[PDB]
C-alpha cells in the first residue's frame, strides 16, 4: 500500500543499515579496557553512577572475561570504564557516519550541512541502534562478544527508570518496532532541519517530512492490531524525548571532560570540545568512499 | 620436649619459609593472561585427557575494588585447551624460584655438592610447590587464594565426588583436613626436599641421614605439641601423604612432557627442572640461581 518512491526509500535505508551496522561487533578491536572545582565532582559522580554497567567479553574459543566495576569509594575509580566507553562510542559513531554517507538524499547535501546534521544526530542514531540489541528482560546490551549489563540496585527498576536514557530504552523496546521503523526513526532524526549550523533548512525539512510520511504509511500497511494503535504518534513522541536526552547527554559529557579528559578526537569534533577546518576527521570521513 | 638441635632445625626451616614464601603473592607480577581472542592424533587425545583436570576459573581483584573473572573454554577442536598454559607456567616458575630460594637458605642443603643440590631440586620442585599451595587452599570454596589472584575449581559435574577422582585435588583436600601447623608444613618440605632416591643423587647416605633427622624432628614435634591420645598416627598419615605426593609428581612430569611435545609452553626454568632440551652444563639457570 506504499508508493514505489516510499518503497525505494525504505529499502535504500534498510540496505544502508545492513551495510553499516556491525550488529555482531566483529570488526571492533584495539579497544581500551579497565586495567587489571569541588562542586563539580558531586554532579559528575551523579552523572556516572546512574550508568553503572558490568562488561562481559566473550572469546571465539568459548572463554568469557567478566569485569565488575569498582563501588564508589570517592574518585578516579568512577572513570575506570570511560576509556572503553569512548572507544565503543567512536566505533558506533563511525558506523552512523557511514550510514548517512550511503543514503542518496544525505550525500547530495552541502558538506557543511552533512557535518551539521551528523553533529546533532550522532548520539541519537547511536541510541536507536543500541536499542535493537537491548535485552529488557536482563537489562543487557548484547553487542556480539561484548555485553553491557546494568548493575543491580536496591532501588529496583524505579531507581534505574529515574535515569532518562534507561527509561527511553525500556519504553522504545516495549513498542516492539520492526527494523523498517527503527531505520525510518534514524532517517527522521538525521534529517532534522533545526539543528545548529544547518543552512538548507527547507531542503532538510522537506526530506524529513517525506520520511515521516513514509513511516506513517508503513505502519498503516503492516500493523493493524489494537496494541499498535497510535504507534506513529508514539514513535514521534519518542523521537522528541530522544532530542531532549541528547541535549542532556551533551551537558553531562562536557562536565566529565572538564574534570577528566577522555573524549576521542572524533567525539571532540562531534560534541564541540570554517566547519570543515574545525571538523577535519568528519570532513575526511565524508569525502572517503563507502 | 625437643632437643636443642631439633628446635634450631625448625627455626632454620621457619626462617627459610618466612624469607622465601610470598604468602600474599604481592611480588608475582607481569604474568601472561588468557587473551580475549596419524600417530600425532593419538598424542593429541592423551593431552586432551591430561588437561581436563585443570577446570579452574581465574579471579583478579583490583586495587580499586574491581574484579576480573575468567571462565576457561570448553574443549572444542583444540588449541583453546592451552589458553591457561602461559599463565600457569608463569605462576609455576614464580613458585619454583621461591622453592630454590628456600633450599638455598638451609645450611644442610648448602653443604651438599651443587650437582646433588640440583638433583634434589629437580625431584622435589613440584612437590614443595604443592605443599605451599595447600596452605592457601580453601577447601570450603575449592579456591586457591593467592592474594589478589584466586583459582576456583569449576563445578564440572556431580561435584565433590567427580573432583576427588583427580589425585591432586584429593591430596589438597586430605592434606587440608589434617589441619597442620606451619612447622609441620615446613618439615614436610624438608623431608620431601632431602629425598635420597631422586634421579642423579650421589651422596645418598648423607641425604638419607638428613631426611631421617627431619622426620624424627617432625615425629617428636607431634608427640610434644599435640594431644597425644588423638594424634597417635598423624606422623604416619603425613608420611603417606608424602608418598602419594611423590606419585602425583611423576604423573605431572609425564603429563607436562606430553603437552610440551605437541605444544611448547615451558619457561626456560621449567625446561631445566623437567628435563626438556654435564649436569652443571645442562642446568645453567639452576646453577646461577644456586650460586647467586
Ligand atoms: C556507561 C553506561 C553504558 C550504558 C548507558 C547508556 N549508553 C551510553 C553510555 C555512555 C555515554 C558517554 O557519552 C558518557 F559520557 F555519557 F558516559 C560515553 F562517553 F561514556 F560513551 C553515552 C551513552 S548506550 O549508548 O546505550 C551504551 C554505550 C556503550 C555500551 C553499551 C551501551
Ligand atoms: C595438569 C595438572 C593439574 C594439577 C592441579 C592444578 N595445578 C597445576 C596446573 C598445571 C600445572 C602445569 O605444570 C601443567 F603442565 F600440568 F599444565 C603447568 F605447566 F601448566 F603449570 C601444574 C599444577 S595447581 O598446583 O593446583 C595451581 C598452579 C598454578 C596456579 C594455581 C593452581
Image: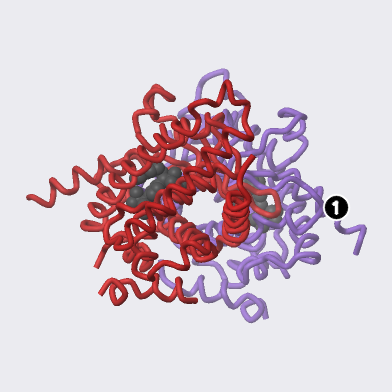
Chain colours: A purple, B red
Compared to residue A266, the image places residue B206 above or below, namely above
Q: What is the x, y in percent for residue A71? A: 73, 45
Residue in the image at 49% along x and 48% along y: B214
| Label 1 element class | helix
Residue to which mark 1 is pinned: A43
Dot 1 crowding, Cα within 10 Å, few <14, some 14–19, many 20+: few
Asked if residue A98 shows in the view, the reply is: no
Name which residue lies at 50% across and 66% down. B104
Q: Is residue A101 left or right of residue B24?
A: left
- Furthest toward the top, the residue is A226
In the image, taking residue B267 as reference, residue B135 lies left or right, namely right
Q: Position of residue A65 (x, y in %)?
A: 50, 47
On what subunit does the disc labeled 1 rest? Answer: A
Q: Examine the rendered structure and indicate whether residue B285 appears above or below residue B252.
A: below
Residue drawn at (62%, 68%), measured in percent from left and top?
Answer: A264
Location of residue A202 (image quadrant): bottom right
Front in this rendered view, residue A121 or B143:
B143
Residue B264 % position (x, y): 28, 61
Amino acid at each position: 500500500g506504499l508508493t514505489e518512491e516510499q518503497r525505494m526509500m525504505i529499502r535504500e535505508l534498510m540496505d544502508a543499515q545492513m551495510k553499516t551496522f556491525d550488529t555482531t561487533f566483529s570488526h571492533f578491536k584495539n579497544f581500551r579496557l579497565p586495567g587489571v572545582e569541588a562542586a563539580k565532582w558531586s554532579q559528575v559522580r551523579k552523572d556516572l553512577c546512574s550508568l553503572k554497567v558490568s562488561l562481559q567479553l566473550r572469546g571465539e574459543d568459548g572463554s568469557v572475561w567478566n569485569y565488575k566495576p569498582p563501588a564508589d569509594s570517592g574518585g578516579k575509580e568512577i572513570f575506570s570504564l570511560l576509556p572503553h566507553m569512548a572507544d565503543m562510542s567512536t566505533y558506533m559513531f563511525k558506523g552512523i557516519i557511514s550510514f548517512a554517507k550511503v543514503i542518496s538524499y544525505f550525500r547530495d547535501l552541502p558538506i557543511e550541512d552533512q557535518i551539521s546534521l551528523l553533529k546533532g544526530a550522532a548520539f541519537e542514531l547511536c541510541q536507536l541502534r543500541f536499542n535493537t540489541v537491548f535485552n529488557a528482560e536482563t537489562g543487557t546490551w548484547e553487542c556480539g562478544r561484548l555485553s553491557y549489563c546494568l548493575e543491580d540496585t536496591a532501588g529496583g527498576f524505579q531507581q534505574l527508570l529515574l535515569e532518562p536514557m534507561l527509561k527511553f530504552h525500556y519504553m522504545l523496546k516495549k513498542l516492539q518496532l520492526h527494523e523498517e521503523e527503527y531505520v525510518l526513526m534514524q532517517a527522521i532524526s538525521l534529517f532534522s532541519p533545526d539543528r545548529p549550523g544547518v543552512l538548507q533548512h527547507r531542503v532538510v525539512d522537506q526530506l524529513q517530512e517525506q520520511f515521516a510520511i513514509t513511516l506513517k504509511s508503513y505502519i498503516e500497511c503492516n500493523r493493524p492490531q489494537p496494541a499498535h494503535r497510535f504507534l506513529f504518534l508514539k514513535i514521534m513522541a519518542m523521537l522528541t524525548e530522544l532530542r531532549s536526552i541528547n541535549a542532556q547527554h551533551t551537558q553531562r559529557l562536557l562536565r566529565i571532560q572538564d574534570i577528566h579528559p577522555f573524549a576521542t578526537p572524533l567525539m571532540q569534533e562531534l560534541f564541540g570540545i570554517s566547519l570543515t577546518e574545525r571538523h577535519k576527521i568528519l570532513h575526511r570521513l565524508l569525502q572517503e568512499g563507502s
